[PDB]
Image (tube, rainbow, N blue to C red; front, side, top):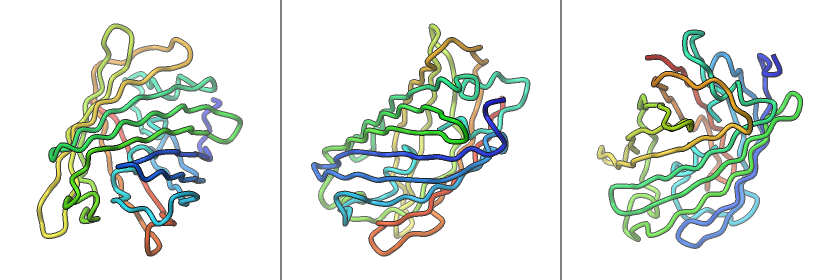
Length: 213
């Protein structure tokens, strides 16, 4: 109801990481009740990007999560009025990103307005040397405190050579209106770049997500 088996996506991200400003625009489509979605992403400003694209992709909507009927679905309940989120991302090698997304809805399409800022990434390091391969597939924790939904997860970039590169994610969400809050619960997270052009100016990005206890 109002969330259809198919929901289009438009987004705009403005940002800076270690000072290089950039804009990225995206258009995709997904199946909210199956928890899957595909986005096509273009770097409109600041190409060629001088850092790992992988630090961005989790910022590119938990309405695309398969929720059992036994767990209230905060994100689908928030529509058509929407919700926002604020996220901190603290990497092990003392680099840090902060991201915001305001998610609205108009018809068959979700719209995101995303702000992404990162700083103090090591020069030799895996992000500004583009040595990340993919995120691992965590299952993170959702929980409520004092009326706000919180969601956070330890995860990690695989590196060229076999190593791993760790990041603590902490997100706080907000619906525009009051909705039923859930139990503490979980959310998987399979995120992979399916395709990209040479400098990740064009990227096809795909996610599968599902909740449980």
